Every structure is written in structure tokens, then in C-alpha cells.
Amino acid sequence: GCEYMTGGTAVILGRVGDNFAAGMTGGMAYVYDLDDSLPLYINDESVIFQRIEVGHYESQLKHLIEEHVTETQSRFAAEILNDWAREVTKFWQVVPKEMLNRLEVPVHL
Amino acid sequence: MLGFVHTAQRMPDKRPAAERRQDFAEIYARFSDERANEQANRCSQCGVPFCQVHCPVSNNIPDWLKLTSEGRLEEAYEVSQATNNFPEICGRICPQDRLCEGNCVIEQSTHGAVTIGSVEKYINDTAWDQGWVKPRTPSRELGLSVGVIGAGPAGLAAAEELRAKGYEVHVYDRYDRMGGLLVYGIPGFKLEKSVVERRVKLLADAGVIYHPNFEVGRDASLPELRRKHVAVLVATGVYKARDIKAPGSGLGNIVAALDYLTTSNKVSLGDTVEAYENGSLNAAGKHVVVLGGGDTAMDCVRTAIRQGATSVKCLYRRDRKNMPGSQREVAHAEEEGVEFIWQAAPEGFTGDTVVTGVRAVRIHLGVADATGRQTPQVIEGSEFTVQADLVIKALGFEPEDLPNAFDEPELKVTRWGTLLVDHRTKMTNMDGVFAAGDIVRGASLVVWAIRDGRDAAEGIHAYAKAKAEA
Ligand SMILES: Cc1cc2nc3c(=O)[nH]c(=O)nc-3n(C[C@H](O)[C@H](O)[C@H](O)COP(=O)(O)OP(=O)(O)OC[C@H]3O[C@@H](n4cnc5c(N)ncnc54)[C@H](O)[C@@H]3O)c2cc1C
Ligand code: SF4
Ligand code: SF4
């Protein structure tokens, strides 16, 4: 998934495949992991996986999932949204190794 | 006579919490006459009245609404009582914010609900206050023996209707003061003990014979009852309890809600029992905890704050919105000075044969599924202890044991324990035995018992005449 992605946003809820984010250059991704099995799948050549700490990205992901559940009337997304405070920590954030210094928002504290 | 465009809604009266926390008197004083003319005029006489559809007894509201708006209280009272027995108490007890005053089209338009309950109460008190009230004796008394088990609202309504029909009915119950649990269960803080004694006096005036202080489960048996009479109607009501078996339960200073309520309110109104000062059902000014979320818990915390000064809390597993009681009741309770805990459940009763505290957890409710249920899940994040010496186990009711224990090896019931009746005739599995009240449906309201009692009386009359045709 997201092979050679260059820009945009891709929110993924659930298990990921193998070799996820292979050759990623730009953009930003979010993954809703449940068993910490992501490090055994993602390719760590040019990307890094971390946790969300800044309130800005938290709010962005919140608004994206809110619009998604408003659009498709999906019950699982609503179950995620109602438990936002608990389930916010399970999310992994995947960021390329090129936007570490070019991002307008500091990705790291 | 629409009116609601310009005039604004306003309840009759509300005594502040300064003097209310002490006495047992009502909270709502009676309704004013100019206010009667003004607020009754407020309705819109809405075609296709939704207020009638949602009312479980389906009485013709807009008729007497317009009448009282114009006066003519005599025919107004006549058309008001022609359809619904026990008008005062049914009007004052109905959770109107969800039954009738919760669907008036003016309320859906956010203008406010027509104060239908207060109009019913007022039109039925003024009518009695000037002697425009008489019993209903049957002309050309046919003469037959019929029996009713249980003096609840359903039994009393069926008895009054059958006495108006031309029969001779006998009322069997377990208590000395007739009138169902109205005189024992419902607190006087919300229903004073004058209207009930007045209405039961009117009943006895019509020519009904009471069998007070009996126990049909012990004093006699259903075959003897049926042999003495021509038809019997079982309306014994529900009186069992559901308790918990948490670690450290069953020890001292725990009790059910019903007994504490009945003694420490009604028998203390009569000043007879000693358990108010002998038993632990007193004003232990330390603390009080109440489990459950039904209306029983609400009246329990109300009467706990009334009886003596204490600091009380309430524990309930669901959320505020799914609570079955009236949201005006919880508002009054919060005004009195009670503290609520939402979405929590008790897991342990810590003590040394005396309850020192309660260990509870916090649960969470997911999103409702297709059927509409919200599954609960414990969190484990915050399991806390709350300090108190007495907890009240108000967890509702459920059908007792009726078939085997009470009288009859031949009596069909469902898995719920409640029995079954026909949607048309209300006749049970056994002939000559009809049912009504809360036995058939479970824990329900008063007006439902009234409707079931009326239907049961009609079916009883029909079946009796059909059998006597031979
Ligand atoms: C605002 C509001 C508040 C309420 N508060 C409460 C509350 O605090 N507690 C509560 O329990 N309900 C409460 N209810 C529910 C309501 O009181 C009942 O659902 C209703 O009164 C049922 O009456 P019934 O006609 O079925 O007879 P019931 O009131 O159920 O009683 C049947 C009658 O049979 C008698 N009886 C019992 N056992 C026997 C026997 N073995 N032999 C002969 N007779 C017997 C009883 O004494 C009673 O007179 C409330 C309802 C409302 C609307
Ligand atoms: S309850 Fe609604 S429909 Fe009925 S008379 Fe009042 S305003 Fe009209
Ligand atoms: S108190 Fe009962 S009868 Fe009167 S309007 Fe409300 S639901 Fe109808």
C-alpha cells in the first residue's frame, strides 16, 4: 500500500499488508493498529513510524474521520470516534524522511 | 382560541427548596382560575390530535380544553371523567413529559407543551370541591358474585366499572388500607393521601364489598374462589425483587427499596410502626447510597433527603438519556441537593458485616446496533470506593412464582414468569380466570393498569352474559 506515494493523505483502519509504504517520498499517513504488529510489516527504508503528539495532526485526523463517518454512515468509524480519547494512542503516524525539516508544522517536539 | 402565538407557557407554581426539603407536602400548588382561562386557551385545537393518540387511555383532550377555555366546567368535568377513571391521580402521576404532554404539536414546534396534566388536575379538583360528584349505583341490580384479587388501580377500576354494570364484586388484598400500592408504594411527597382515600370512599359508596387483610395465597385457594363466585380476575401485581451477589453482600445494613419506602413514609404518616426507630431505616446523617435507575431509585433518594438530613448519592449503569423516569424528576432531585453518578455499577460491598463502603467500576456504551442496543463494557481504569453505611437495592421487580406457589398447578405462563391473556378477551388459560394490571405486562405505569382494567371489566361482562345465555 501507498507504494511510491508523493503527496496527500491516506487514512487506513485495520490490518495492513506486507511491504507497506515502499518507496514513499512525500505526504503523510495514519494507521489504526490494534496489536503493535505494524513494525513487522512496514518498510523502514525512507519512512519512519511514530506516535501522534502534536494537537494539530490529532485535530486533522479527527476531522477526516468525522467527515468519513458523516459521509458513509459507517458504524465502525462511529465506534472509533466515540472512544477517541482511548483509541487516539493506538494510531501510528507514518512520515517520510524528507519532510522532517520542510514541514510547516514541527512534526517532532 | 389558538392563543399560543402571543401568550407564553408557565407552570402553576413551585415551592423553593428552602422549605420543601423538610416537609412532606406537595411541590405543586393548585392552578389559578385566570391561569386556567389563559393556559387552556393556549392549545391550538389541532386537527388529528397527537395528544389523543399517544395517551394510553385515549381521552378527548381538546374538547374539555376548549370548554375550560370558555368555562362551562360541569359538562367539561362530565366529558373528562366519562372515559378515564381516577382522573386526579392519573393526571398527577402520568409522566406527561413523555406520554401526552410530550407529543402536543405545539411542543414539537418548540413553542412549549400545553399543560394538559395541570388542566386535568384542576378540572377534577374544582369539580369535586363543589359537590358535583356522585357514585354510580346500578339500576335493576342483576345480582351475581364476582371476585377480584388485588386492590391495585386496575382492580379498583374494574370493580367500579363492574359495579356500574350491575354485578356484585368482592375485593381481596393483603393490606389493611385499600387502594393498591398507591397508599403504600407511591410516596406522599408526590401524591398526598387524601385523594386516594376520597376515591376509595366513593367506591365503597357505590355498593362494593371489600375483603381487607386477606391472603389469597394462604387464606383460601383459587378453586374455592371460583366456586364462590361466577368469575374471578387476578390482578395480584408484582412484588418480587432482583438482588446482586457481589463479594461481601448479604451482611448488615442492606435492604430492599420497597419495604423502606412503605414503612418509613406511609406508616410514619400513620405513626404506628417501631422499625422507623428500631430498624436502620432512619436518618443516619452519615451517608446513603441507592442502586438502580428506575423511578423507584428517584423516589427513594427523594424520601431519603426528606427524612432527616444526609448526603446521598445514586449509582446507575446506563446514561442520563436512557433513564426511564421523567427528566423533571431528576431536575427536582438535583434542585434538592442530591448527587448523581452516571454510567457506573457496583462490584463489591466492603465491610465487616456492616457496610463500610461500595467498590464500583465505570462502564462505557458503544454505538447502537441495528436493533438499537448499546452494549456496556467495563473500563477497569477507575475502580473507586464510595463511603456509606446503608445502600438501597432498587433493581426493579419480576413475576413472583404464580402458577405453582400461589394456587394453581393448571396455569400457563411464559419464560418471563408472567402469564398470558388474549388480546381480545383478556381471558387466561383457565376458564373463569381473567387477568389485568401489571402481572401481564411487567413493571408499567398507572394509566396502563387503568386501560387494562377497563378492557378486562368489559370482557368479563361479555363472557358472563354469554355463559348465562344458557
Ligand atoms: C410516577 C410513577 C411512579 C411510580 N413509582 C413506583 C414505585 O415507587 N414503586 C413501584 O413498585 N411502582 C411504581 N410505579 C409503578 C406503578 O405503581 C405500578 O406499575 C402500578 O401501580 C401497578 O398497579 P396494579 O394495578 O398492577 O396493581 P399493583 O399496584 O401492582 O398491586 C396489585 C395489588 O395486589 C395486591 N397483592 C399483592 N400480592 C397479593 C396476593 N398474594 N394476594 C392478593 N393481593 C395481593 C397488592 O397489595 C396490590 O394492592 C410508578 C409509576 C409511576 C407512573
Ligand atoms: S395537545 Fe396538541 S393537538 Fe391536542 S389540543 Fe393541544 S395543541 Fe392541539
Ligand atoms: S395524565 Fe394520563 S390521561 Fe392525562 S394527559 Fe397525561 S397520559 Fe393522558
Image (tube, grey):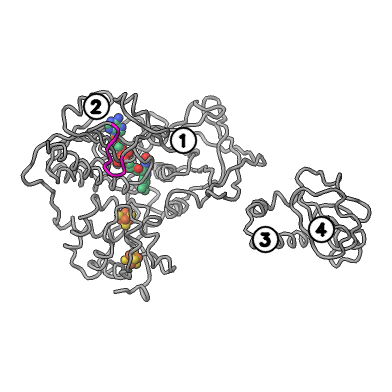
User: What segment carries the magenta color?
Assistant: B422-429
Residue identifier under label 4: A29
Q: Nearer the viewer, residue B223 or B208?
A: B223
Residue assigned mark 3: A66
Marks 4 and 1, how far apart at CA = 52 Å
Secondary structure of the residue carrying numbered label 3? helix
Q: In this view, does B366 lie to the left or right of B57?
A: right
Hey, what amino acid is under mark 2? Answer: Leu
Pointers 1 and 3 in contact (CB under 8 A)?
no
Q: Position of residue B131 (x, y in %)?
A: 13, 55
Give A61 or B191, whichever is nearer the viewer.
A61
> Which residue is denoted by mark 2 in the rendering?
B222
Q: Please state which of the two labelled residues, at mark 4 or mark 1, is closer to the viewer.
A: 4
Q: Residue B447 carries which label?
A: none
Residue at the farthest left position = B140
Quadrant of residue B351 within the rendered picture: top right
* Mark 3 neighbour class, 10 Å CA radius: few under 14, some 14 to 19, many 20 or more: some
Residue B460 image point, x, y percent: 21, 40
How far, Cα to Cα, is label 4 from label 3? 17 Å
Residue for badge 1 = B393
